[PDB]
Image (cartoon, rainbow, N blue to C red; front, side, top):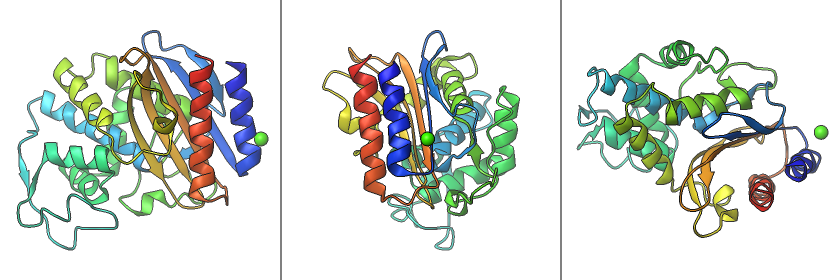
Length: 263
Ligand SMILES: [Ca+2]
């Protein structure tokens, strides 16, 4: 809707820097609206939905096991690890690790999962394998949220991310069981309050994952819809701004309020 596009362009002037936007029909895959659709933005924690996508994929192939118990040391714990910092002696399962990464953006969990598959380039090779020759993860947490200007490392484009998420959520890549699991994790997202969720009305469904970076980087990928079912995929990204994480949060919630108003 033209109005939401006007509000995205307004968000950019307000925040400074760059804002990327795309709205996609879940069933058709049709692009409804867009802004800087083919430009690169640092992925940030949003990549974790792609990681667990890769992981579930190996489970589906009988190569991985969600119940498999992984162990780690205190040197594995990097910044921000609400869950993993609790289970140093326990260990955690691939499942619980994926649950931590998506529902809590646990950075250490994400690192552990990355190891199970061989790291950044392996995740990228997964992306490349499924038709996404644009998205790329190069580093680990937390260096990947660095978002240096004009650095194509750990970046994606709105359209690239949006269509990849769609393939993961609805395609024939992942079994039904795994497609359900991945969206269950995203619906159980607990660290994305002041974004799309804060504009979402009662009755509406939302499965999402947010991200925060340096240099005012901020992002979110979501599957949302009314009537308790998802029907569109929304992807928002921003970086290069000096505005605080609130003025950024507020601009995302507003973009959200607008996509809902002109549904
Ligand atoms: Ca502008």
